Amino acid sequence: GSATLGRLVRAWPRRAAVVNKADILDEWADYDTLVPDYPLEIVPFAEHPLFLAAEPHQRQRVLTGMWIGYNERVIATEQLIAEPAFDLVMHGVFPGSDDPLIRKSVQQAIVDESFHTYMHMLAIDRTRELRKIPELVTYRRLRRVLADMPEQWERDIAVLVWGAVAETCINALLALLARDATIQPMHSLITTLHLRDETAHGSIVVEVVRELYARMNEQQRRALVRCLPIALEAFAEQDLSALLLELNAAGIRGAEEIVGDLRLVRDFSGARKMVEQLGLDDAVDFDFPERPDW
Amino acid sequence: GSATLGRLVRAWPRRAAVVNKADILDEWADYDTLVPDYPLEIVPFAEHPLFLAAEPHQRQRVLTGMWIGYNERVIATEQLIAEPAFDLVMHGVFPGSDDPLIRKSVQQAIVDESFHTYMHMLAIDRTRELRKIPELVTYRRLRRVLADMPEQWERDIAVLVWGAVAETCINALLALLARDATIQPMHSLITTLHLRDETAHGSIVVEVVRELYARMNEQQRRALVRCLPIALEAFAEQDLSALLLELNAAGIRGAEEIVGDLRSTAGGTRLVRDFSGARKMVEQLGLDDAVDFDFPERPDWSP
């Protein structure tokens, strides 16, 4: 059995956010309204003259809004992309998925994603309380690939690939929020805890997908190589529709102009590994972006 | 919001099996092969002449297969029935289900179910390795009901009710294996942890279903009322097809004759699910008299 999987399975009790910070709720103890919810320098339009010309409380509303919006996207991703890929691995629908080490490592990740959703949901609800307060462009794609596949087995591949990519391509905001010493300490803790788990999830996915693919027959093998670039591009795309809603919700005049001038890349390093591990360096038409410093 | 739910949600970090025994894998460290996987005391047909006429290793094969089959059904019930009901609540498909407290309680329970599936899966795999080793009837009944409902809103109700019955009506094997000192210590530990979690889940389901039912439109209310007896009877039904297969695997002659009513141990201990919690749920809904179901007597072993 995979020695990486083995190591990650034995290490899970010491590493996992769920085991070690289940009492995340408590972190809103000695609360300070005086710290912002989101870092200014990570906001795409932070420097726009129509933004900077908004009133202090308007800007602060936008930052709060985007902290919230980020948690909503995280939850959507786990529930709609990531978990379902893990679930399919656990339903035993792919050859080679009965292996006990795959079952252990993947089900631990399922526990992790459930707790991630809890952490982020708590963060939304606590923020909305203390601050007195749109479909993902990755899920919409997915729903449209599936709608044109008449056989279950092919939908299985698409779900699997979409989840694998989601789990190996780290959101810049996750790593940026984790290390930010200027925002609410519980915002950077939640994101740090999530990043710690997500690191192991990337290694896990690379192993599992390597094993399933080796054991996929041909309709499943060629299905997968087709799907990957469609999935990777979907996580590469940029829709600023969410930015527009946050701007309008804060009543920022010229919201459309700001977004218009706009017209944070994921760390595709894990998906690159996964491609090399599957031996597909030359077979997938995608231009892997330069690795970030985070 | 509900005081009871407030306290369950604050208790979850102290109480949850996932936080108490994440290192459950390590529990197989000084495994003793001589110690049985399942308690003979608890086997409905333990004293059948044909079960006694078998050889001792054949009876041990049956005991191990019964432990495995138990874990397999737990996993199926969680994956196919309990989680999908919790998942619907978290998707906001019911009026009033966007309550932060409801959301907190149900997402905590979802973390729990995911860990329960982990432990039971671990038990199967470790057992199958160390011993060198069909459709749930309740899910079959569910599928039939759903296949004949035209509208999503009504299938949502049905999924919700079936999930609530599963989570309020404690499996007898869960409670009896939990307290059993004669079997592998990891087996009684896993079921003790799951039992601790499940007791809280029953209380949570009662609060949540009451808050949801209160907010449902009239046809949703009517749908839930129709569904309850269907679910209660599905779960009051034990299937013997699995047992039958174990006996045959062990090579025991006259399997069909051996497996009788599975509703009692030979000593008289009740093996039907503890319907206590679903009775409380029906009361909280004000439905004691609108639901046509004869609840069995509460068993001594009830949580």
Image (cartoon, coloured by chain):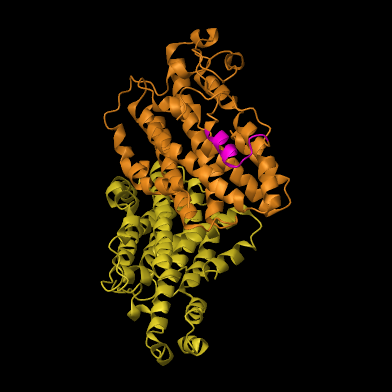
Chain colours: A yellow, B orange
| Residue A194 in view here | yes
On the picture, is A54 further left or further right than B81? left
Magenta residue check for B283 = yes
Q: Quadrant of the N terminus of chain A?
A: top left
Foreground pick, A62 / A172: A62
> How many numbered marks are there?
0
Q: Position of residue A218 (x, y in %)?
A: 55, 55
Foreground pick, A139 / A125: A125
Q: Position of residue A44 (x, y in %)?
A: 40, 82
Residue occupying the point 30% across, 65% down? A31
Residue A99 appears in which quarter of the rendering? Answer: top left
Q: Position of residue B290 (x, y in %)?
A: 68, 37
Residue occupying the point 70% across, 41% down? B226
Report the magenta residues as a range. B277-289
Magenta residue check for B64 = no
- Please name the predominant secondary structure of the magenta segment in the image: helix
Foreground pick, A3 / A136: A136
| Residue A99 in view here | no
Residue B128 to residue A101: above or below: above
Q: Quadrant of the C terminus of chain A?
A: bottom left
Residue B247 to residue A189: above or below: above
Foreground pick, A227 / B91: B91
Q: Position of residue B180 (x, y in %)?
A: 38, 23
Residue B50 appears in which quarter of the rendering? Answer: top right
